[PDB]
Image 1: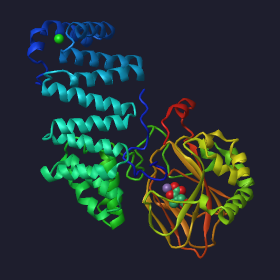
Image 2: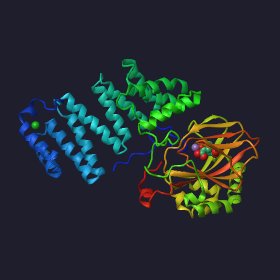
Image 3: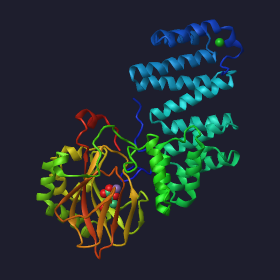
Image 4: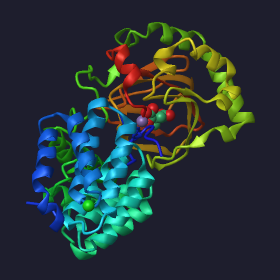
Length: 18
Length: 429
Ligand SMILES: C[C@H](CC(=O)O)C(=O)C(=O)O
Ligand SMILES: [Cl-]
Ligand SMILES: [Mn+2]
Protein backbone atom coordinates (compact mmCIF):
# COMPACT_ATOMS: atom_id res chain seq x y z
CA UNK A 1 0.00 0.00 0.00
CA UNK A 2 0.84 3.70 -0.04
CA UNK A 3 1.31 6.18 2.81
CA UNK A 4 -1.16 8.86 1.76
CA UNK A 5 -2.65 10.45 4.88
CA UNK A 6 -0.81 8.29 7.40
CA UNK A 7 2.34 6.31 8.21
CA UNK A 8 0.81 2.84 8.36
CA UNK A 9 3.10 0.94 5.99
CA UNK A 10 6.42 -0.53 7.08
CA UNK A 11 8.09 1.61 4.39
CA UNK A 12 6.53 4.46 2.42
CA UNK A 13 9.05 4.68 -0.45
CA UNK A 14 10.03 2.10 -3.06
CA UNK A 15 13.61 0.88 -3.47
CA UNK A 16 15.11 1.36 -6.94
CA UNK A 17 18.82 0.89 -6.26
CA UNK A 18 21.15 3.77 -7.04
CA UNK B 1 36.37 -13.50 14.56
CA UNK B 2 34.55 -15.18 11.62
CA UNK B 3 36.09 -18.32 10.13
CA UNK B 4 36.02 -17.64 6.39
CA UNK B 5 38.74 -20.03 5.13
CA UNK B 6 38.16 -23.71 4.41
CA UNK B 7 41.04 -26.20 4.26
CA UNK B 8 42.14 -25.29 0.74
CA UNK B 9 41.71 -21.53 1.23
CA UNK B 10 44.12 -21.67 4.17
CA UNK B 11 46.82 -22.90 1.78
CA UNK B 12 46.34 -19.91 -0.56
CA UNK B 13 45.91 -17.30 2.18
CA UNK B 14 48.91 -15.32 0.90
CA UNK B 15 47.27 -14.78 -2.50
CA UNK B 16 43.87 -14.06 -0.94
CA UNK B 17 45.38 -11.47 1.42
CA UNK B 18 47.22 -9.72 -1.41
CA UNK B 19 43.96 -9.31 -3.32
CA UNK B 20 42.02 -8.15 -0.25
CA UNK B 21 44.77 -5.66 0.59
CA UNK B 22 44.10 -4.02 -2.79
CA UNK B 23 40.40 -3.68 -1.96
CA UNK B 24 41.05 -2.17 1.48
CA UNK B 25 43.41 0.40 -0.08
CA UNK B 26 40.61 1.57 -2.38
CA UNK B 27 42.24 0.18 -5.55
CA UNK B 28 38.91 -1.42 -6.36
CA UNK B 29 39.50 -1.94 -10.08
CA UNK B 30 42.83 -3.63 -9.35
CA UNK B 31 41.16 -5.63 -6.58
CA UNK B 32 38.40 -6.93 -8.86
CA UNK B 33 40.96 -8.07 -11.43
CA UNK B 34 43.07 -9.76 -8.75
CA UNK B 35 40.13 -11.68 -7.29
CA UNK B 36 38.87 -12.50 -10.79
CA UNK B 37 42.31 -14.00 -11.42
CA UNK B 38 42.07 -15.98 -8.18
CA UNK B 39 38.59 -17.19 -9.14
CA UNK B 40 40.02 -18.16 -12.52
CA UNK B 41 42.94 -20.01 -10.92
CA UNK B 42 40.99 -21.46 -7.95
CA UNK B 43 37.39 -21.75 -9.23
CA UNK B 44 36.29 -23.70 -6.13
CA UNK B 45 37.68 -21.23 -3.56
CA UNK B 46 34.85 -19.68 -1.50
CA UNK B 47 37.05 -16.89 -0.14
CA UNK B 48 38.19 -15.94 -3.65
CA UNK B 49 34.57 -15.92 -4.84
CA UNK B 50 33.51 -13.79 -1.86
CA UNK B 51 36.38 -11.39 -2.50
CA UNK B 52 35.21 -10.99 -6.09
CA UNK B 53 31.67 -10.31 -4.88
CA UNK B 54 32.85 -7.78 -2.29
CA UNK B 55 34.92 -5.96 -4.90
CA UNK B 56 31.98 -5.90 -7.33
CA UNK B 57 29.91 -4.58 -4.42
CA UNK B 58 32.44 -1.81 -3.78
CA UNK B 59 32.65 -1.08 -7.51
CA UNK B 60 28.87 -0.67 -7.73
CA UNK B 61 29.09 1.90 -4.92
CA UNK B 62 31.92 3.74 -6.68
CA UNK B 63 30.15 3.89 -10.05
CA UNK B 64 26.60 4.03 -8.57
CA UNK B 65 25.69 1.22 -10.97
CA UNK B 66 22.70 -1.07 -10.49
CA UNK B 67 24.14 -3.37 -13.16
CA UNK B 68 27.47 -3.79 -11.37
CA UNK B 69 25.55 -4.54 -8.17
CA UNK B 70 23.45 -7.17 -9.98
CA UNK B 71 26.71 -8.90 -10.89
CA UNK B 72 27.81 -8.82 -7.25
CA UNK B 73 24.44 -10.25 -6.19
CA UNK B 74 25.03 -13.26 -8.46
CA UNK B 75 28.61 -13.75 -7.24
CA UNK B 76 27.43 -13.76 -3.62
CA UNK B 77 25.11 -16.62 -4.59
CA UNK B 78 27.96 -18.39 -6.39
CA UNK B 79 29.86 -18.43 -3.08
CA UNK B 80 27.01 -20.45 -1.56
CA UNK B 81 27.07 -22.97 -4.43
CA UNK B 82 30.73 -23.92 -3.96
CA UNK B 83 31.88 -27.03 -2.08
CA UNK B 84 33.04 -26.86 1.53
CA UNK B 85 31.95 -23.28 2.28
CA UNK B 86 32.52 -22.32 5.95
CA UNK B 87 29.30 -21.55 7.80
CA UNK B 88 30.38 -18.01 8.69
CA UNK B 89 31.17 -17.22 5.05
CA UNK B 90 27.98 -18.85 3.77
CA UNK B 91 25.89 -16.72 6.13
CA UNK B 92 27.82 -13.51 5.39
CA UNK B 93 27.52 -13.98 1.63
CA UNK B 94 23.80 -14.77 1.50
CA UNK B 95 22.98 -12.03 4.03
CA UNK B 96 24.74 -9.41 1.90
CA UNK B 97 23.05 -10.86 -1.19
CA UNK B 98 19.62 -10.32 0.37
CA UNK B 99 20.58 -6.86 1.63
CA UNK B 100 21.68 -5.75 -1.84
CA UNK B 101 18.61 -7.33 -3.44
CA UNK B 102 16.44 -5.18 -1.16
CA UNK B 103 18.50 -2.11 -2.08
CA UNK B 104 17.69 -2.80 -5.74
CA UNK B 105 14.01 -3.39 -4.96
CA UNK B 106 14.24 -7.13 -5.70
CA UNK B 107 11.98 -7.91 -2.77
CA UNK B 108 10.87 -11.32 -4.06
CA UNK B 109 14.50 -12.20 -4.72
CA UNK B 110 15.54 -11.12 -1.23
CA UNK B 111 12.73 -13.22 0.26
CA UNK B 112 13.94 -16.37 -1.50
CA UNK B 113 17.45 -15.66 -0.20
CA UNK B 114 16.18 -15.13 3.35
CA UNK B 115 14.09 -18.31 3.20
CA UNK B 116 17.21 -20.19 2.09
CA UNK B 117 19.18 -18.70 4.99
CA UNK B 118 16.53 -19.76 7.53
CA UNK B 119 16.50 -23.27 6.04
CA UNK B 120 20.31 -23.44 6.22
CA UNK B 121 20.57 -22.05 9.78
CA UNK B 122 17.40 -23.21 11.58
CA UNK B 123 18.58 -22.11 15.05
CA UNK B 124 19.52 -18.54 14.05
CA UNK B 125 16.59 -16.43 15.22
CA UNK B 126 18.16 -13.22 13.92
CA UNK B 127 17.81 -14.71 10.44
CA UNK B 128 14.12 -15.39 11.08
CA UNK B 129 13.81 -11.76 12.20
CA UNK B 130 15.40 -10.73 8.88
CA UNK B 131 12.97 -12.98 7.02
CA UNK B 132 10.05 -11.26 8.74
CA UNK B 133 11.37 -7.92 7.48
CA UNK B 134 11.45 -9.39 3.98
CA UNK B 135 7.76 -10.26 4.24
CA UNK B 136 6.98 -6.81 5.64
CA UNK B 137 8.76 -5.13 2.72
CA UNK B 138 6.52 -6.89 0.17
CA UNK B 139 3.40 -6.17 2.24
CA UNK B 140 2.91 -9.77 3.41
CA UNK B 141 1.90 -9.07 7.00
CA UNK B 142 0.31 -12.51 7.42
CA UNK B 143 3.55 -14.38 6.73
CA UNK B 144 5.57 -11.81 8.67
CA UNK B 145 3.28 -12.37 11.66
CA UNK B 146 3.83 -16.14 11.53
CA UNK B 147 7.60 -15.64 11.46
CA UNK B 148 7.68 -13.37 14.51
CA UNK B 149 5.30 -15.70 16.35
CA UNK B 150 7.81 -18.49 15.72
CA UNK B 151 10.65 -16.31 17.04
CA UNK B 152 8.68 -15.25 20.11
CA UNK B 153 7.81 -18.90 20.80
CA UNK B 154 11.54 -19.67 21.08
CA UNK B 155 12.85 -16.38 22.55
CA UNK B 156 9.86 -14.54 24.08
CA UNK B 157 11.92 -11.48 25.08
CA UNK B 158 13.46 -10.80 21.65
CA UNK B 159 12.94 -7.04 21.42
CA UNK B 160 13.28 -6.89 17.64
CA UNK B 161 10.59 -9.55 17.31
CA UNK B 162 8.38 -7.75 19.84
CA UNK B 163 8.30 -4.36 18.07
CA UNK B 164 7.74 -5.97 14.67
CA UNK B 165 4.99 -8.20 16.05
CA UNK B 166 3.44 -5.16 17.74
CA UNK B 167 3.70 -3.22 14.49
CA UNK B 168 1.79 -5.98 12.66
CA UNK B 169 -0.90 -6.23 15.36
CA UNK B 170 -1.31 -2.44 15.23
CA UNK B 171 -1.61 -2.48 11.43
CA UNK B 172 -4.31 -5.15 11.88
CA UNK B 173 -6.28 -2.76 14.16
CA UNK B 174 -5.45 -4.95 17.19
CA UNK B 175 -4.63 -1.77 19.06
CA UNK B 176 -4.78 -2.89 22.69
CA UNK B 177 -2.88 -6.08 21.87
CA UNK B 178 -0.10 -4.19 20.08
CA UNK B 179 0.78 -1.82 22.94
CA UNK B 180 2.67 -4.24 25.27
CA UNK B 181 4.73 -5.57 22.35
CA UNK B 182 5.67 -2.13 21.04
CA UNK B 183 6.35 -0.86 24.56
CA UNK B 184 8.36 -3.85 25.82
CA UNK B 185 10.25 -4.06 22.53
CA UNK B 186 11.35 -0.42 22.57
CA UNK B 187 12.22 -0.74 26.27
CA UNK B 188 14.46 -3.76 25.56
CA UNK B 189 16.94 -1.54 23.73
CA UNK B 190 17.70 -4.47 21.45
CA UNK B 191 19.43 -3.60 18.15
CA UNK B 192 16.81 -2.48 15.65
CA UNK B 193 14.18 -1.33 18.16
CA UNK B 194 15.34 2.32 18.38
CA UNK B 195 13.21 3.17 15.36
CA UNK B 196 10.84 6.09 14.81
CA UNK B 197 8.18 3.82 13.30
CA UNK B 198 7.73 2.00 16.61
CA UNK B 199 7.61 5.20 18.69
CA UNK B 200 5.09 6.58 16.18
CA UNK B 201 2.68 3.66 16.37
CA UNK B 202 3.01 3.02 20.12
CA UNK B 203 2.01 6.62 20.79
CA UNK B 204 -0.81 6.41 18.27
CA UNK B 205 -2.08 3.12 19.73
CA UNK B 206 -2.01 4.65 23.22
CA UNK B 207 -3.89 7.72 21.96
CA UNK B 208 -6.59 5.49 20.45
CA UNK B 209 -7.19 3.63 23.74
CA UNK B 210 -7.03 6.83 25.80
CA UNK B 211 -3.66 6.12 27.46
CA UNK B 212 -2.26 9.48 28.58
CA UNK B 213 1.29 8.08 28.48
CA UNK B 214 1.21 8.49 24.68
CA UNK B 215 2.90 11.89 24.73
CA UNK B 216 5.68 10.72 27.05
CA UNK B 217 6.58 8.35 24.21
CA UNK B 218 6.36 11.13 21.62
CA UNK B 219 8.64 13.20 23.87
CA UNK B 220 11.20 10.38 24.15
CA UNK B 221 11.06 9.73 20.40
CA UNK B 222 11.78 13.43 19.92
CA UNK B 223 14.67 13.30 22.40
CA UNK B 224 16.15 10.31 20.54
CA UNK B 225 15.97 12.18 17.22
CA UNK B 226 13.08 10.37 15.54
CA UNK B 227 10.66 13.33 15.58
CA UNK B 228 11.27 17.01 14.87
CA UNK B 229 8.94 17.69 17.81
CA UNK B 230 6.26 15.97 19.86
CA UNK B 231 3.70 17.55 17.51
CA UNK B 232 5.48 16.95 14.17
CA UNK B 233 6.09 13.22 13.83
CA UNK B 234 6.66 12.63 10.11
CA UNK B 235 9.50 10.21 9.36
CA UNK B 236 10.43 11.07 5.73
CA UNK B 237 11.82 14.56 6.17
CA UNK B 238 14.15 17.20 4.83
CA UNK B 239 15.86 18.92 7.74
CA UNK B 240 15.61 22.68 8.08
CA UNK B 241 12.20 23.25 6.48
CA UNK B 242 10.14 25.87 8.31
CA UNK B 243 7.84 24.03 10.72
CA UNK B 244 4.51 25.52 11.78
CA UNK B 245 1.02 23.96 11.94
CA UNK B 246 -0.92 26.68 10.09
CA UNK B 247 0.15 28.73 7.04
CA UNK B 248 -1.26 31.77 5.27
CA UNK B 249 -1.24 31.94 1.45
CA UNK B 250 1.35 34.73 1.52
CA UNK B 251 3.58 32.65 3.82
CA UNK B 252 3.54 29.80 1.28
CA UNK B 253 4.28 32.04 -1.70
CA UNK B 254 1.65 30.06 -3.66
CA UNK B 255 -0.68 33.04 -3.88
CA UNK B 256 -1.50 32.51 -7.56
CA UNK B 257 -2.63 28.93 -6.89
CA UNK B 258 -4.74 30.09 -3.92
CA UNK B 259 -6.36 32.86 -5.98
CA UNK B 260 -7.17 30.37 -8.75
CA UNK B 261 -8.77 27.93 -6.32
CA UNK B 262 -10.83 30.64 -4.65
CA UNK B 263 -11.81 32.49 -7.85
CA UNK B 264 -12.87 29.23 -9.54
CA UNK B 265 -14.16 27.30 -6.51
CA UNK B 266 -17.69 26.79 -7.85
CA UNK B 267 -16.59 24.81 -10.91
CA UNK B 268 -14.52 22.59 -8.62
CA UNK B 269 -17.53 22.11 -6.33
CA UNK B 270 -19.87 21.40 -9.25
CA UNK B 271 -17.63 18.72 -10.75
CA UNK B 272 -17.30 17.08 -7.34
CA UNK B 273 -21.07 17.10 -6.88
CA UNK B 274 -21.58 15.66 -10.37
CA UNK B 275 -19.29 12.75 -9.49
CA UNK B 276 -21.12 12.27 -6.18
CA UNK B 277 -24.41 12.09 -8.07
CA UNK B 278 -23.46 10.24 -11.27
CA UNK B 279 -20.17 8.43 -10.62
CA UNK B 280 -20.05 7.89 -6.86
CA UNK B 281 -17.86 4.78 -7.20
CA UNK B 282 -14.95 7.11 -8.02
CA UNK B 283 -15.00 8.08 -4.33
CA UNK B 284 -13.03 5.37 -2.56
CA UNK B 285 -13.27 4.82 1.22
CA UNK B 286 -10.27 5.89 3.28
CA UNK B 287 -8.17 2.77 3.79
CA UNK B 288 -5.39 3.67 6.28
CA UNK B 289 -7.34 2.78 9.48
CA UNK B 290 -7.57 6.48 10.38
CA UNK B 291 -11.27 6.55 11.39
CA UNK B 292 -12.66 5.80 14.81
CA UNK B 293 -16.10 5.72 13.16
CA UNK B 294 -18.07 7.19 10.29
CA UNK B 295 -17.78 7.55 6.54
CA UNK B 296 -14.93 9.28 4.70
CA UNK B 297 -14.07 8.76 1.03
CA UNK B 298 -11.75 10.39 -1.47
CA UNK B 299 -11.72 10.95 -5.23
CA UNK B 300 -8.08 11.36 -6.24
CA UNK B 301 -7.01 13.35 -9.33
CA UNK B 302 -3.20 13.29 -8.76
CA UNK B 303 -1.02 11.08 -6.60
CA UNK B 304 2.78 10.89 -6.43
CA UNK B 305 2.88 13.63 -9.06
CA UNK B 306 1.02 11.47 -11.60
CA UNK B 307 -2.27 12.52 -13.17
CA UNK B 308 -5.02 9.89 -12.94
CA UNK B 309 -6.41 10.14 -16.46
CA UNK B 310 -9.63 8.22 -15.78
CA UNK B 311 -10.29 10.35 -12.70
CA UNK B 312 -9.71 13.56 -14.65
CA UNK B 313 -12.36 12.46 -17.14
CA UNK B 314 -14.77 12.98 -14.23
CA UNK B 315 -13.45 16.43 -13.28
CA UNK B 316 -12.01 17.70 -16.58
CA UNK B 317 -12.27 21.44 -15.89
CA UNK B 318 -10.74 21.06 -12.43
CA UNK B 319 -7.85 19.03 -13.86
CA UNK B 320 -7.40 21.57 -16.65
CA UNK B 321 -7.28 24.39 -14.09
CA UNK B 322 -4.78 22.61 -11.84
CA UNK B 323 -2.38 21.72 -14.68
CA UNK B 324 -1.14 25.33 -14.58
CA UNK B 325 0.39 24.78 -11.11
CA UNK B 326 3.35 22.36 -11.06
CA UNK B 327 3.89 23.19 -7.38
CA UNK B 328 0.97 20.82 -6.73
CA UNK B 329 0.68 18.59 -9.82
CA UNK B 330 4.40 17.82 -9.57
CA UNK B 331 4.35 17.20 -5.82
CA UNK B 332 5.44 13.56 -5.80
CA UNK B 333 4.91 13.45 -2.00
CA UNK B 334 1.31 14.63 -2.12
CA UNK B 335 -2.10 14.24 -3.70
CA UNK B 336 -4.87 16.30 -5.26
CA UNK B 337 -8.23 14.88 -4.25
CA UNK B 338 -11.83 15.54 -3.33
CA UNK B 339 -12.61 14.44 0.24
CA UNK B 340 -16.17 13.79 1.42
CA UNK B 341 -17.00 13.19 5.07
CA UNK B 342 -20.40 12.40 6.56
CA UNK B 343 -21.94 12.98 10.01
CA UNK B 344 -20.85 10.67 12.79
CA UNK B 345 -17.21 10.65 11.64
CA UNK B 346 -14.16 11.05 13.85
CA UNK B 347 -10.69 10.85 12.31
CA UNK B 348 -8.08 9.71 14.85
CA UNK B 349 -5.26 12.14 15.66
CA UNK B 350 -2.58 11.33 13.12
CA UNK B 351 0.41 12.65 11.22
CA UNK B 352 1.34 12.45 7.54
CA UNK B 353 4.48 10.66 6.38
CA UNK B 354 6.60 13.66 5.31
CA UNK B 355 7.42 17.27 6.17
CA UNK B 356 8.06 17.97 2.47
CA UNK B 357 4.47 18.96 1.66
CA UNK B 358 1.89 21.49 2.79
CA UNK B 359 -1.82 20.80 2.43
CA UNK B 360 -4.45 23.19 1.10
CA UNK B 361 -8.14 22.59 1.83
CA UNK B 362 -10.68 24.40 -0.34
CA UNK B 363 -14.17 24.38 1.16
CA UNK B 364 -16.85 23.24 -1.31
CA UNK B 365 -19.93 22.15 0.68
CA UNK B 366 -19.53 23.00 4.37
CA UNK B 367 -22.50 22.54 6.73
CA UNK B 368 -23.01 25.56 8.97
CA UNK B 369 -22.25 23.55 12.13
CA UNK B 370 -20.47 20.41 13.21
CA UNK B 371 -17.31 20.19 11.06
CA UNK B 372 -13.90 21.13 12.42
CA UNK B 373 -10.22 20.28 12.08
CA UNK B 374 -7.54 20.53 14.77
CA UNK B 375 -3.87 20.86 13.87
CA UNK B 376 -1.54 20.78 16.87
CA UNK B 377 -3.16 22.95 19.55
CA UNK B 378 -5.43 24.96 17.20
CA UNK B 379 -8.87 24.03 15.86
CA UNK B 380 -10.41 25.67 12.79
CA UNK B 381 -13.29 25.14 10.39
CA UNK B 382 -13.71 25.37 6.63
CA UNK B 383 -15.54 28.01 4.61
CA UNK B 384 -17.09 27.49 1.19
CA UNK B 385 -14.82 29.00 -1.46
CA UNK B 386 -11.93 29.66 0.95
CA UNK B 387 -8.57 27.89 1.32
CA UNK B 388 -7.09 26.67 4.61
CA UNK B 389 -3.40 25.70 4.68
CA UNK B 390 -1.70 23.49 7.25
CA UNK B 391 1.32 21.21 7.57
CA UNK B 392 -0.16 17.74 7.99
CA UNK B 393 3.18 16.47 9.31
CA UNK B 394 1.82 17.99 12.53
CA UNK B 395 -0.72 15.93 14.44
CA UNK B 396 -4.22 16.70 13.22
CA UNK B 397 -7.72 15.44 13.91
CA UNK B 398 -11.14 15.91 12.30
CA UNK B 399 -14.76 15.67 13.46
CA UNK B 400 -17.94 15.64 11.37
CA UNK B 401 -21.09 16.05 13.50
CA UNK B 402 -23.26 18.00 11.03
CA UNK B 403 -26.63 16.92 9.61
CA UNK B 404 -25.45 16.53 6.00
CA UNK B 405 -22.30 15.83 4.01
CA UNK B 406 -19.14 17.96 3.98
CA UNK B 407 -17.11 18.16 0.76
CA UNK B 408 -13.64 19.73 0.48
CA UNK B 409 -10.93 19.84 -2.19
CA UNK B 410 -7.42 18.89 -1.00
CA UNK B 411 -4.37 20.26 -2.83
CA UNK B 412 -0.91 19.21 -1.62
CA UNK B 413 2.04 21.41 -2.59
CA UNK B 414 5.79 21.08 -2.19
CA UNK B 415 7.05 22.75 0.95
CA UNK B 416 7.96 26.20 -0.43
CA UNK B 417 11.54 26.12 0.92
CA UNK B 418 12.44 22.98 -1.05
CA UNK B 419 14.78 23.82 -3.93
CA UNK B 420 14.03 22.67 -7.49
CA UNK B 421 16.84 20.10 -7.17
CA UNK B 422 15.10 18.50 -4.17
CA UNK B 423 11.72 18.52 -5.91
CA UNK B 424 13.18 16.47 -8.78
CA UNK B 425 15.15 13.96 -6.69
CA UNK B 426 13.13 13.19 -3.54
CA UNK B 427 11.63 9.67 -3.63
CA UNK B 428 7.90 9.70 -4.26
CA UNK B 429 5.58 9.05 -1.32
C1 LIG C 1 -9.26 14.03 7.74
C2 LIG C 1 -8.61 15.06 6.82
C3 LIG C 1 -9.21 14.92 5.42
C4 LIG C 1 -10.59 15.59 5.38
O1 LIG C 1 -10.96 16.36 6.31
O2 LIG C 1 -11.35 15.37 4.40
C5 LIG C 1 -7.10 14.77 6.82
O3 LIG C 1 -6.67 13.89 7.47
C6 LIG C 1 -6.15 15.62 5.97
O4 LIG C 1 -6.66 16.51 5.24
O5 LIG C 1 -4.90 15.43 6.01
CL1 LIG D 1 39.98 -24.73 -7.05
MN1 LIG E 1 -4.47 13.72 7.43
